[PDB]
Image (cartoon, coloured by chain):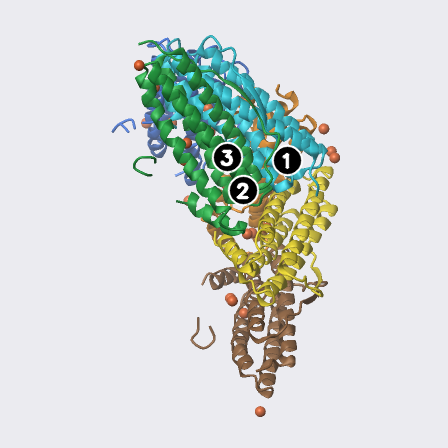
Chain colours: A orange, B yellow, C brown, D cyan, E green, F blue
């Protein structure tokens, strides 16, 4: 029952993505309140940072503990340019989340090729949260194309944060 | 991360099946009480109509909202012949439910061929409810081969309706 | 006390209307969230779909069970064109609801001509829900002529859905 | 929708494994308290016996009831040699549990080759409990390499038994 | 106070009987629902399987722990033929239960011949459950000679399962 | 009331330290359970990771929001060598925590030199948590010099984690 080295590497790379994304999203959350004057958009993005630098990363380490796989910590992230407005900050988050979806799909395809059924099971969480976290992000992006008032958008975000689907929750 | 057109079509066809089945099952529920004098068999079939014209159909539209897929509404259903007895009405429901199982299997096979792992996840609900809803139907069919009294059968159906397995519930 | 064949036909046609309307309204609810970015307008229209494909249809079948009338299921519905904006989607719903009012009036007139007093009683529910469901729809249509912000309108719809008159409730 | 004979056989063989393992684990639990003077290690192994001779076996029979598959009961188990110490008794349990993992993987691979998506769904429970039950076992094995006192180990086992992960629980 | 080798052997043989009976009764419970369409008769027989493969077996191992006796695990059971109907399945269970009574009597006679008063005490539980478990079984057998309807019998079994005498409970 | 650029830089460097420390401590927590077989030592170090990558980092960004200071995200961390035992893993954490104390002292000295009294106030939290978090770490280090049993140490850590001083809490 020996562990696939290719999955270890793909999952160590997913650990990295999640760590680094959450570190950018912590900055973007700072920028959303500070520069863009939108406190609740930052709360939304802070909650994403904490999801990524949290359960998304810890589930990988736990799996590794159980399967014999090794953890690798190599992190390199710099926020050197910030988007111009808040619409674009949330659109950037989206872009990154759609990319998470593409990476997760690759781990699933590999698990099936390596006949690792425990890794395919493990990734099913990530297959689902991929669409979910993007759906959440899209719903905020939508708002910026539905109002020209930042204060109306901000109140809609409030309620969204101050709120589980049977398939995707 | 662009959507498979073949899955959209298979899932738009599953939406249609569920809409149309529930419309037949609403008729069959009417017929079970009206013509066949079995009120609780109709309650069982009304509950199936409502499952199909409900969650089975709405989960598809929600997925579509999230993935970029399009909804299509083309419905054509007519109940032109009704079964002769109640045993046969429930046996007809069974037949249709075993066919749901075969259709769902095809969506799963395609998702794996198209490498759509989010659609394979989505269909896992339907893989499971396929067997479940058939199991429920079979359990009523069984009754008609275990009694010659419609009133005993009816009381067994009562209790069954007036009632979640860890794998299939 | 033998049943009027003309009322059976008018009520079998009303069953059809309600089934088919609810199937269009389920699509329109999908479109209101998906394309038009208005989640709560779709919840409003989903609630209408469920009313029509529910109590409006089931009360007819129950009556039929009691009076000797026959149910007919012949459904043909296709959504081939969708309105351009959300104002027009709700204005289309209105149009269809004002037409329900005209059809219900015809069943009432016929019942009185056929001296079916039980059908006139039965239709009194529909006489009342006709104006009610239109009033509800008009109240949403009004909003689109009172704001240019989709997000303000959406919050007014929220509260309206997240809410019985002594004559019309 | 006709049942795969190869899955029936693989699942009838898994039924056998679980029955026979639980019968050995009931003996090993006896031996852990009686000969090895470790009451709580036996409680841990008695709880495994009961899991195997319980839900692991009953879920297979239930599935069979639903899919048309046949149950086969052919059991042959003898405990003819017992390990020398308790470290080795738990290490033997581990070995057997890692083998369960390998067998479950084979059922999954076959289900995908036979295009049995309901069997792949069914086995997902077993894919998960495979790693879980091994993780539990490893955690006890670990203790024997962390203390030379059987009474300290025994108290750690106590607390472990006298205690659900979102992916593996 | 040294242990009788003859009682150890008789009680190791009783352990075997109980293990093997419960494994047949688990099959028969499967067959009662699956083939014979009687879900509650199988629940009754599943409850017997669990009694035998449970307390009947564990009390022997516990005694052994206390008296110095050895446990032996040698199990060989195959279900190669199933009864034709449900009356006969329950009549087969009866036969096997009346045989339990005869075996238990022999352990008691031996204990008194070996002057093992602690084994005579221990067996008093089994002397009592022998008649009890047979009484329960007879009460179900009776039903099959009192109705020709499987659905009436099934409802009587339901209530019996969904239910302690001062001497036999 | 214009912000000191030197404090911004020192506090942006403290943000970096805390992010990077928590990422190493997440690895070390993995290693403490996985390799060193000490689950509760890892829980202790996971709790430190979360403190650092949490409140220690967020309080800096909040301050920045209020004072006009800029956030900088430049992270570079790699775990390339792991300590040999668990005593040394906790001794490494200590070393790093005593270094936090030295860095915090420097921010305080600078604030007083720059006459930034709001930054001196802000740092008072960090002056205090410096000694506290080290005290906590020392208390675990102590254990490894007080027992040779990893399982006794582990139970002492359990209780410590499963547990506010008026000056340092
Ligand atoms: Fe604020
Ligand atoms: Fe979340
Ligand atoms: Fe393959
Ligand atoms: Fe997430
Ligand atoms: Fe009725
Ligand atoms: Fe249901
Ligand atoms: Fe492929
Ligand atoms: Fe269903
Ligand atoms: Fe939504
Ligand atoms: Fe309503
Ligand atoms: Fe008149
Ligand atoms: Fe209505
Ligand atoms: Fe004891
Ligand atoms: Fe368990
Ligand atoms: Fe294939
Ligand atoms: Fe298990
Ligand atoms: Fe059942
Ligand atoms: Fe009992
Ligand atoms: Fe004597
Ligand atoms: Fe018993
Ligand atoms: Fe653990
Ligand atoms: Fe803390
Ligand atoms: Fe000064
Ligand atoms: Fe701290």
- Marks 1/2 in contact by CB < 8 Å: the verdict is no
Label 1 secondary element: loop
Q: Residues within 10 Å of mark 3 (few under 14, many from 20)?
A: many
Q: Is residue C169 above or below residue E118?
A: below
User: Spatial distance from mark 1 to mark 3, Cα to Cα?
Assistant: 21 Å
Q: On the image, numbered disc 1 is attached to which residue?
A: D70
Q: Indicate the chain on which mark 3 is placed.
A: E
User: Spatial distance from mark 3 to mark 2, Cα to Cα?
Assistant: 10 Å
Label 2 secondary element: helix
Toward the viewer: A45 or F64?
A45
Q: Quadrant of residue E111?
A: top left
Q: Indicate the chain on which mark 2 is placed.
A: E
Image label count: 3
Disc 3 Cβ-to-ligand 20 distance below 8 Å: no
Q: On the image, numbered disc 2 is attached to which residue?
A: E87
Q: Are both tags, 1 and 3, on one chain? A: no
Asked if residue D68 lies left or right of residue B154, the reply is: right
Q: Is residue A44 visible?
A: yes
Toward the viewer: A31 or D167?
D167
Q: Residue F26: where, in percent of width, then height?
A: 48, 24
Q: Give the quadrant of the N terminus of chain F.
A: top left
């Amino acid at each position: 029952m020996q562990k696939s080295n290719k999955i270890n590497d793909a999952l160590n790379q997913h650990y990295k993505l999640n760590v680094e994304l959450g570190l950018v999203y912590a900055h973007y959350a700072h920028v959303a309140d500070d520069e863009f004057d939108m406190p609740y958009l930052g709360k939304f993005i802070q909650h994403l940072s904490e999801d990524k630098l949290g359960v998304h990363k810890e589930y990988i380490s736990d799996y590794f503990k159980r399967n014999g796989m090794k953890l690798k910590t190599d992190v390199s992230v710099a926020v050197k340019s910030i988007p111009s407005d808040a619409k674009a900050l949330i659109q950037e988050v989206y872009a990154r989340e759609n990319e998470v979806r593409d990476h997760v799909k690759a781990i699933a395809k590999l698990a099936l090729a390596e006949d690792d059924y425990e890794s395919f099971y493990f990734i099913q969480w990530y297959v689902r949260d991929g669409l979910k976290d993007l759906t959440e992000v899209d719903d905020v992006v939508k708002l910026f194309n539905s109002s020209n008032d930042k204060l109306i958008i901000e109140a809609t975000i409030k309620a969204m944060v101050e709120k589980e689907h049977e398939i995707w929750g």
